[PDB]
Length: 76
Image (cartoon, one colour):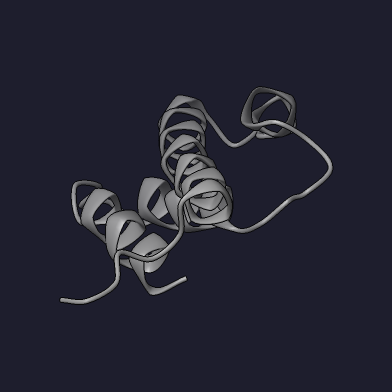
């Protein structure tokens, strides 16, 4: 879970404007019922929100899957 937050914050730092940064955080929140492309269809507050929501959703969902299939690197 900490790895997810780190990678999401890394992307969110690239959105210097308030609305896309918040849309990044929104897209990175868990939705175990839908894909990123299904979820971003509901974003209606403009193209910068669409882009950031989708990008951070994509990053977060990829890390969720990696955490499930491989998980934490141990022994460091």
